[PDB]
Image (cartoon, rainbow, N blue to C red; front, side, top):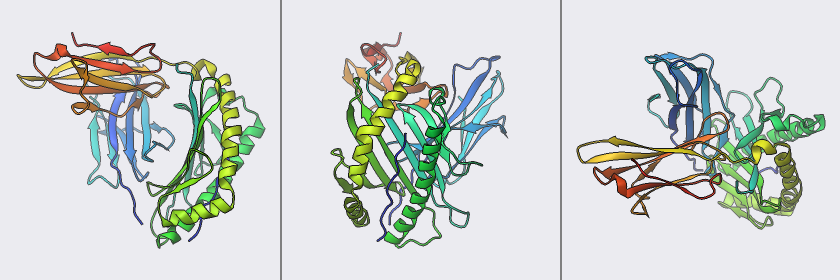
Length: 387
């Protein structure tokens, strides 16, 4: 359940991040069995992006995508997907265009007891094209359960998980109202922030908000969060004591003084210690058969010679939930952090996640390397060695 957010105060630099692209199937592809083709685009900023799935060079028409969300560094991620039945010869790919790319990039298809709730908000101004685009999503751990999009035909808080559908009309009305109010608050924040940095109305800017709570196995608050970012950079954050702010620059300090006088932190603390933890506890009980079940990774190692004297060892983890995982390659038990290539953890589309880690080793020394896997679904870490 949401909270109404404060407005940045009236009184420049901008991050650009290039998308990371992975193309893959949800489950091992079968030459005659239905599957899902996934294109996962992550780590990018700003949020404007174009993603198409290709079949034999042709653009696939019925492609869905996940609701815009972002990672701790404020960078965005999206999953694009479609059901498909792969064949021996049909060739699939993903094409991505973004301001950081000089041409569209084509990639060919080759527990613990602790929990969290987060709401993520993204407002993006659209100069000359109407009002800002407002998109908000809510998560329990790595399970999305609501979304709100100001460009929907009838914008409202919408269910995205089965265990939230039982909430009554008061819940949907209340959270829809909070979203609609926050849309207008964000529009006012964007206007105020332009003034703080002497920016005209002609440029597009991004205002992102996150808040939420972490609880332990007994349901107690472990810590609360509320942070804001402008154009991809930290702007102001509630400190861990839930009683003070950290402001990134002189503009944000003006907001800090306004929110101090308005006792914003006290209101957020009240929400984080009460409503946030109480509703998270409710969701964990109502969705316990999925939310309180950890799925351990299914793991294996592959081996690819790259020359007469070196080979690639790749450690795969598949089908795990929640998304947090650690894959490490060791030589004689010592971490090879510098030499290990990792990919961003990616969604299969069915709640679970996937990840791999690779290392290049001298041919003949493969047996001195082990892959170490840590996941909360494992009683103890797993170790794998190539045969």
